[PDB]
Image (tube, coloured by chain):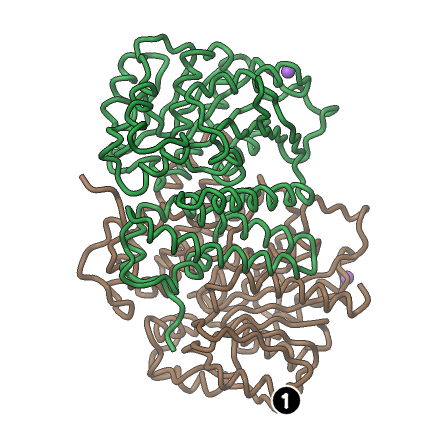
Chain colours: A brown, B green
Amino acid sequence: NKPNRISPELLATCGYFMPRIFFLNSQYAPQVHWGDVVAALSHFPAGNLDLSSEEFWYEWMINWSKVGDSYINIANSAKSEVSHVRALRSAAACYHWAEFMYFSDRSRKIQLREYIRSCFLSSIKYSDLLVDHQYIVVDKFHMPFFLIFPKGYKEEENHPLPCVILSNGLDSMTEIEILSLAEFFLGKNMAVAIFDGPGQGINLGKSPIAIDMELYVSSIVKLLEDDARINSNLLCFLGISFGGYFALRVAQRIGDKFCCIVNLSGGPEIAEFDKLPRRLKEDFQFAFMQDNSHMQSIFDEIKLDISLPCKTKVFTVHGELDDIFQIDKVKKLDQLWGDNHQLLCYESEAHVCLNKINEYMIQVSDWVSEQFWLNGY
Amino acid sequence: NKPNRISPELLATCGYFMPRIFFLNSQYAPQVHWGDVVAALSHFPAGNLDLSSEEFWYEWMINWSKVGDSYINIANSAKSEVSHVRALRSAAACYHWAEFMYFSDRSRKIQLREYIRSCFLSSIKYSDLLVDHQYIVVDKFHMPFFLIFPKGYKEEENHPLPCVILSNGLDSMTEIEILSLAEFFLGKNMAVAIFDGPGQGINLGKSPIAIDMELYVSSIVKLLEDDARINSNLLCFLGISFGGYFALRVAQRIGDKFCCIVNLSGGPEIAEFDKLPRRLKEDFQFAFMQDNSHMQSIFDEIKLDISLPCKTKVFTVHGELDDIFQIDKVKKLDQLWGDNHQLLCYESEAHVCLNKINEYMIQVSDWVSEQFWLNGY
Ligand code: NA
Ligand code: NA
């Protein structure tokens, strides 16, 4: 017999996604172990190596679902709460990687995100963090909302805290990548606000993603203004990916509500829809609940007027080799926005600069703390 | 330009070691991110793919040292203690993977382990764990010793705690792999005792590793007997690898001091020295501070008398395809030791079953809790 291993062909093919799958070493957010990737890919069918093909991502979903199922079995039989929670977190991570680039069964994708959300709410019960979970009603939309306080937080022993609002990207899950980013701010004794806007988190495939997400961010700001535990004069908005695009929108429309805004590899406009690589066409189609023929028009509407003023301090992290948000458009925005925009550009990094995420989140978290200090914290 | 990536040839070649390098997702123990492996291997010289060659592990040490240096630079410039500690942990992990399979410069290897230990002691200052660091004097040997208490531990608000003593393997570092394992017991409100015996941790390359490590474990037991904070009637010994061999020795010589013992892929005897794969000959040579010609005699002395009685409950985790501690010898011990020995055997796993470490440490930690409960906890 040969030891369980990932095929050389497969591991190389998946190189772009391995930094995404491992993401950030986290205390609360679900995260895979190397062994989970081996469990998912060790029996992956050979001759199936096309990242743009529906058949690849079907087998990916099936194989990652099996690893998630194995962790639920461990969770169900766990002899302690601490063991139960670790198994649930592992299951949630596996189900996320099963679903994040799978679009061909809407009901199956929604089912997997519901599994993750169920695992998350169960993890909160046994956690040592204060989580305020509620719906924010925006017009007819009931927005899932999580206000999370730092370890050992007591309202009676604290002044009002600074708060970072973090947005999902196109294919992130709120309790996975976003909670992972959020831990950098929780670690610095800041509150964090994470949320499921239309077409985001648990709403992906249920409601179309809203281009004007700043409308939903405004409703979060009003909640934080009313909450005595939060210093509404010390607010940051952070977006990753498409969420970074929302970060640029927030900067233009409601920037004066924020001490600073962080844009993790969002841009003022997306590359031509027709020529998008890998599964990105189906990804954008699924998020917007639209077909191929309607997407370039949406991209045209998405494109920002970079002449419109930036109303706060913006920090952008971007890769020179980003094929979704081209660096030239970000650099054009950087020059135009001038003293109010700082660009950290990684010369040999692809979209989201995920080989640098540990180092840049250290730098980003310290930069946000600095902006709060500059506003008299 | 092309994005920074690990060569397909290199990633496949290193398959055996990738589960070791990632190890366990940990809160305190230093751990790499995927991006750190990319930083180490993205500019690794081509045509250098022999895991048994001195030249491969030299370039490995050089390239991992560069990533460690980068994190020390981040640590030195960090604007917060939380950022400082995260950078130090990342540096420590990188320096460990630089040194763990590098033996050709004794002074350089010792220097890298000193860097790790310096980073660790600095991390303790800012940590939320009570660490009792001292020397245990055994004869003329001054043994580095760490007694670590669970999160939020107060002697006044607790009964005497159970304690797990964990041993290094041949090439582990105490604050990396062993602290990673230890977190499973800290999570269950147990004390943990981690230590640098002769030829272990900081002493690797300074003093020859002691075959009779149980002598040093006895001195830890006496300390725990004297400490009012520890319930000396609720003690576990866990060893990984060669440390698992020590676990079997402890079971035979001082088992009656322990409610239970865990053997993570140790065995009663090692495979023929001459035919050991990869860098294992140089690994054993370095640990024992002996040349090739003397090692088979040491292996002959190492071999246990499995007829000698097992004096407590033993749990062994072992891979069918282990090429260092052959499964046949473990299964022979399992049958002989009978009701006092439990074997978890993974059919398609290599040495230490590292593709299963998350799931088996959940099972192992729950098993240890169960043994304490059976002894009236
Ligand atoms: Na407020
Ligand atoms: Na005691």
Q: Secondary structure at mark 1?
A: loop
Residue at 65%, 41% in the rendered image: B124
Residue at 50%, 34% in the rendered image: B206
Q: Which quadrant contains ligand 2?
A: top right
Give the vertical position of B195 relative to A147 (above or below).
above
What residue sits right under mark 1 in the picture? A308
Residue at 41%, 32% in the rendered image: B289
Q: Residue A315, percent across and down?
A: 62, 74
Q: Residue B135, percent across and down?
A: 63, 26
Q: How many marks?
A: 1
The type of residue carrying mark 1 is: Leu
Give the vertical position of B323 relative to A270 (above or below).
above
- Can residue A83 be spotted in the picture? no
Q: Closer to the camera, A318 or A144?
A: A318
Q: Residue A278, percent across and down?
A: 32, 72
Quarter of the figure that contains the C terminus of chain A: bottom right
Left or right: residue B261 versus residue B143 is left
Give the vertical position of B40 relative to B133 (above or below).
below
Left or right: residue A279 versus residue A200 is left
Residue at 50%, 59% in the rendered image: A177
Q: Residues within 10 Å of mark 1 (few under 14, many from 20)?
A: few
Quarter of the figure that contains the N terminus of chain A: top left
Q: Residue A244, percent across and down?
A: 55, 73
Q: In the orientation shown, which residue stands out farthest toward the bottom? A: A307
Q: Chain of mark 1?
A: A
Q: Is mark 1 within 8 Å of ligand 1?
A: no
Q: Quadrant of residue B326?
A: top left
